Image 1: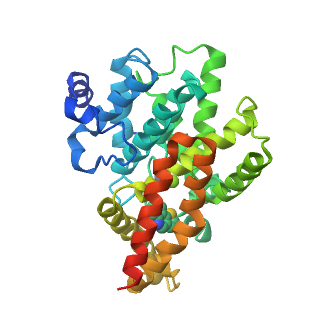
Image 2: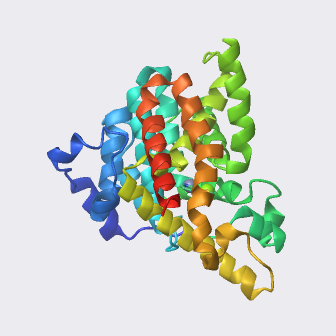
Length: 321
Ligand SMILES: c1cc2ncc3ccsc3c2cn1
Ligand SMILES: [Mg+2]
Ligand SMILES: [Zn+2]
């Protein structure tokens, strides 16, 4: 784990967010893309708005964030920008559903969203497992996601970073278990089971947010909705993020080609024409069901389902030349 220099974390404490942005940040379709220098600060703003201006030591929160930012790599998609996009979509969800969640959950989730793809190397779980990478050794299933939570704990545990230390001991364990579970749920592989279970609970009318296991599933889906929120932005933001996503896919493909292995068409840059159909399969099979389940469960999240439906209708218009 890398530590942020003293110069970095102090600049953030001073940061004041344009009052004209405070209005936009509250919207689901909000895009953070055009605001790079203000990401660390927009996240602090989000923390304070959601869990109070006295959630954490500001000196610690700022240390933590800048060090988190530092342990995200410069790969094309799974980078610092993505971590913050996911945190924002979660803030937007938390904000619209505030009391359904405890104060320890809100702070748990915001941080897990920031921390969720920490130290990503731009390679899928499959890859690492297929070619027996040390990380596949260390972690059998949900490989990257386990490493991310490893990193989350290994930052929390740096001199003066532990924004949770003033929690009671039963609250500290409690909060780190939200974090663990939320992160693990960003393993898309686990999402389809989760989604499927929750759907039933709903239809039956036997879904029960008091019941912990149910809550843990609802949080699971929230994490997936958040991880995928590229697809709920305005068409040109969506098109542009998709570019960065595939840039990473292709660069994973490139190493498999290099290795005399043919990559799936998703990770093969010489199969660009299949992307519009690739997208249309992902949206039908994954995103739509996701936001469709999230909106039955937490109805304020409608405009996420609405936006995704809009961008689906758009990939269609690219299939027709
Ligand atoms: C946004 C768009 C996407 N399009 C395709 C695929 C495929 C795997 S994750 C993913 C994806 C994730 N976020
Ligand atoms: Mg991930
Ligand atoms: Zn992610």
